[PDB]
Image: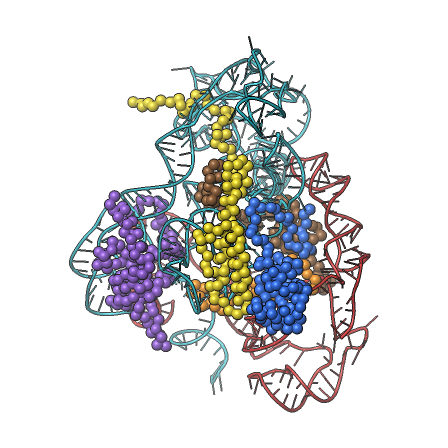
Chain colours: A purple, B brown, C orange, D yellow, E blue, F red, G cyan
RNA sequence: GUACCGAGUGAUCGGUGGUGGAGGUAGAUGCAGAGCAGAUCUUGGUGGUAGUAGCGAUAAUUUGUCUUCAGCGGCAAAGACUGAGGAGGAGAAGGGUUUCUUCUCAUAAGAAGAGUGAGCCGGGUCUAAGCGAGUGUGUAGAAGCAUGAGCGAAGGAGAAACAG
RNA sequence: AUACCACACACAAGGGAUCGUUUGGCUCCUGGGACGAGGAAGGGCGCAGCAGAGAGCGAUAUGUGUGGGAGCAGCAGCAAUGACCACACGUCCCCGAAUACAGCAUAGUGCUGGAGUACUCCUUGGAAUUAAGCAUAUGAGUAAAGGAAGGAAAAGAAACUAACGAGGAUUCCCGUAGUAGCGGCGAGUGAACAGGGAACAGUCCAACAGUGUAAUUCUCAAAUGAGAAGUUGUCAAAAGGAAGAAGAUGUGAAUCAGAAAGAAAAGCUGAACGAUACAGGGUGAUAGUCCCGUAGUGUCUUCUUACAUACGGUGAGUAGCUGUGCUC
């Protein structure tokens, strides 16, 4: 049960809040679980998927496959994974997008600011965990 | 006759664009606008509630009024270079 | 006619720049849902009231 | 070349005015390479950012020049005080609101009370 | 006195105040000129009549245009004519005190 | 939703086979914006009449030839007509790109470009009949009345250009 | 009836009912009640690499600073030398109260004007309608038109009720009451005190200011002087505080596998695990354990509020009266 009356439980309101999200709230939509080993290598339980990271598909047509993330579509919430595609009548191949939550991370791309992003989150935990 | 043949003579134009309201209703001979009463200081009485709500505050852009509300929320902080003047006052 | 005031001329200039179809590249954009520009006009079918 | 704010803040008003004529000359040259010939889409963006930065840094330096002048004076020019709104500028100060005596109580003040219980 | 001003040629009316800070350089040569026009229509005018054609800011007048050219490009000017076009652009035509110099200035400036 | 078949005096109810692609009832009670053939009813969609009634006042049209791809479209040669108070050549009021080039039929249709240069031409000046801010008096506020800055003619007055 | 006209059934046309769905509406409750001469509200015109409308912004038309951090939806180009977002600031074209103006106050600085007006206060003031007709009356001191202010506004501490063994400012709720009465005594209209509660608070001016000296307010100087207002009368004292409330934001448990079948399992079947969290939303069919939250817990920022002097019993074109008009 919910006892805070400032938070809404309306279906109409929850749905609008989802689809009209922007900025950091949009980034929260692209989160995926880490594998059991990585959850010992790092403190975090889940992270936003980025290009170059390595993922196992755990639901759908392409179940059991593994591959590298090629692109991240923020407007239509989908991820393109290397080697997951369909062939047209022409023989031409189109990558099919997968929803973030159907993936699981196997190796992290550590290019750019990723190491600082991870550090910032670990500290935020401990700050309140140790109190 | 009063129908089609009299329509041919209708080539003069009594109203032009008003400079206060835009509404092509300034009568040149009378020296008055039929939408907004220019050049009188106050705006005209609008005929009914339906017609007046079409020209109220919030039907356009409200540029100044919006900024004022944001500044009031922030506590009227002013330009940060000049904080010392603010603080003294 | 040939004699015009400055106020009448600016109204004609603005009424002439607005009278154009949707550019052909916009139709390819993922989020774009318009078919035809409903604000297009013809001199044979409407008056500007520039007077 | 993309000018940076912290690396301009070191110049005098006399030096910054020199820089402005160059940026404006460069903008003219850009417009010609658009009517005539062909332009990379990035060029007009970069041209226009450079003028805006110089005008922003000049304005700050002139405000400081005015601050040093009037800081300690009576009759500060209005523009140096924050705008607020017309009614907040005309309000009475909190001292002035409390000097009046026009219907104030004799007894029944906050000061005439004791800390007591009831049983 | 208040009047609707529908027959007037100047759309501005109000007299302008002073200000505590004033804008750095003011209405000045590099605001006045926009670009020179180089196409088959303009090319003939350089070759036959020693005149260049330019787009200029709406706020500009004959005297200002004369000064701005002599400042940016450097040749001396005989005449300036002006034309408000149906596309909302003010065009200026500038004739130089010596012909032949028109082809020199046009080529240096990359108009032609 | 659509064909069949069964149950009920009847309002209605049940099953079977194709179509459809994600929700739905049976019993007992509660609240109602709770059942249509009609109102010269309201809104939207479709017939018969019917390949029918009509589409042709005015000067009039023929032949060859090229395109067009099937335009009495263009060009040559004939035959006519308006007949200088013209079906000719120009301005104003009104319209506003309808003007020029290219392409396409989508055609009294579109799309993309280009085009209007003044000391001497007209406006910005003067004043007609007249209108009027402010001030005075009046009114709950107005209207009205006295005086009066400013305004009032692209065909009245009004410095100076013509050929190629 | 060979071929026309009608009806039934199957297939193809023609139209958009029905069923399934919804980032919209409506109603009730709670907060808020924030404009303008420092140029508003409202109108116009410009600004994109390819850009008509709409959105955003002013010739600085995606600038500066802080907190974050990954892409910019098409095509070409950009981006850890910061893509994009959030908070504040800087810049902010022309018309418009539109003002180089009008009226007005001070020793001086100045103030007003226009916008909005659901709710509150002050004026002015109908007719349709009901009376089974209609003229007094009704609808109604309502509609319409004008003036003015605030987050509420108005009212308010008895020249008050009552006749009890009396009460004790104003406003609001239950009630006296469809009563006492008003009325072609027709149609119809119509209050007050009590008794039970919410919330509670009282005070100022004049009459009436030290005369062994206006002791009072303001300006410039100066470290103690000049000047303005005022004798048609100026001047009657305290800092000070912790509480109370509203927002913003951090953290936050626990799952795997399978026959058949499907485009896809979260369904179904077996085995587990969390709960101070089984509110609700998203994921390719119906998910406590896949994602965002929720229960529980931390931080921070704003706002509101608080001690001093002297007094009484005569406030006039008023109360009242005569005539007159409206009103209850
Ligand atoms: Zn108007």
* Viewer-nearest residue: G55 or D15: D15
Left or right: residue B80 compared with residue B12: left
Residue G85: give x, y in percent of width and height. Answer: 41, 54
- The residue under the point 57% across, 68% down is E108
Left or right: residue G18 compared with residue G260: right
Residue B62: give x, y in percent of width and height. Answer: 52, 49
- The residue under the point 53% across, 53% down is D17
User: In the rendered view, would you say E2 is above or below E59?
Assistant: above
Kindly indicate the quadrant of the structure image that contains residue G23.
bottom left
User: In the rendered view, would you say D97 is above or below F128?
Assistant: above
- The residue under the point 52% across, 50% down is D13
Residue F64: give x, y in percent of width and height. Answer: 65, 91
* Viewer-nearest residue: C16 or F31: C16
Residue G224: give x, y in percent of width and height. Answer: 55, 21
Instruction: Examine the rendering and report whether any part of residue E86 can be seen.
Output: no
Q: Which quadrant would the C terminus of chain E be assigned to in this image?
A: bottom right
User: In the rendered view, would you say G238 is above or below G14?
Assistant: above
- The residue under the point 28% across, 56% down is A46
* Viewer-nearest residue: F88 or F15: F88
Total marks in image: 0
């Amino acid at each position: 049960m919910k006892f805070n009356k400032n938070v809404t439980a309306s279906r109409r309101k929850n749905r609008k809040a989802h689809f009209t999200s922007i900025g950091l709230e949009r980034t929260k939509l692209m989160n995926a679980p880490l594998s059991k080993d990585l959850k010992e290598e790092y403190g975090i339980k889940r992270i936003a998927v980025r290009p170059g990271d390595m993922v196992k598909v755990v639901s759908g047509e392409f179940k059991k496959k593994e591959g590298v993330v090629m692109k991240v579509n923020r407007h239509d919430i989908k991820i393109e994974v290397e080697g997951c595609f369909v062939q047209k009548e022409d023989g031409k191949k189109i990558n099919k997008g997968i929803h973030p939550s159907n993936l699981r991370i196997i190796k992290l791309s550590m290019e750019k600011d990723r190491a600082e992003i991870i550090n910032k989150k670990v500290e935020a935990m401990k700050s309140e965990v140790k109190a | 006759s009063k129908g089609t043949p009299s329509n041919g003579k209708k080539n003069k134009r009594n109203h032009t664009t008003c400079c206060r309201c835009g509404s092509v209703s300034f009568h040149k001979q009378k020296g008055k606008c039929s939408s907004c009463a220019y050049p009188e200081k106050k705006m005209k009485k609008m005929q009914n509630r339906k017609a007046m709500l079409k020209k109220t505050t919030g039907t356009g852009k409200m540029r100044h009024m919006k900024k004022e509300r944001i500044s009031r929320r922030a506590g009227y902080p002013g330009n940060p270079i000049l904080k010392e003047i603010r603080n003294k006052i | 006619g040939s004699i015009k005031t400055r106020r009448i001329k600016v109204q004609l200039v603005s009424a002439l720049k607005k009278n154009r179809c949707i550019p052909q590249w916009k139709r390819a954009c993922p989020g774009f849902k318009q078919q035809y520009n409903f604000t297009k006009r013809s001199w044979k079918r409407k008056t500007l009231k520039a007077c | 070349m993309k000018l940076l704010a912290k690396d301009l803040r070191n110049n005098s008003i006399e030096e910054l005015e020199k820089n402005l004529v160059d940026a404006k000359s460069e903008m003219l040259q850009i417009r010609q390479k658009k009517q005539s010939a062909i332009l990379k889409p990035n060029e007009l963006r970069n041209g226009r950012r450079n003028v805006a930065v110089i005008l922003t840094i000049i304005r700050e330096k002139k405000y400081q020049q005015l601050l040093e002048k009037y800081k300690d004076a009576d009759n500060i020019p209005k523009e140096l005080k924050p705008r607020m709104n017309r009614r907040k500028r005309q309000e009475l100060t909190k001292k002035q609101k409390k000097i009046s005596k026009v219907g104030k109580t004799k007894l029944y003040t906050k000061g005439n009370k004791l800390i007591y219980a009831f049983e | 006195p208040k009047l609707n001003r529908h027959k007037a040629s100047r759309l501005d009316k109000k007299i302008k105040q002073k200000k505590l800070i004033e804008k750095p350089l003011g209405f000045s040569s590099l605001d006045i000129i926009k670009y020179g026009i180089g196409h088959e229509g303009a090319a003939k005018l350089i070759e036959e009549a020693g005149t260049l054609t330019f787009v200029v800011d709406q706020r500009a007048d004959k005297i200002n245009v004369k000064k701005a050219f002599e400042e940016i490009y450097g040749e001396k000017v005989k005449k300036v004519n002006i034309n408000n076009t149906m596309k909302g652009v003010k065009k200026a035509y500038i004739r130089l005190v010596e012909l032949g110099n028109a082809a020199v200035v046009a080529t240096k400036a990359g108009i032609l």
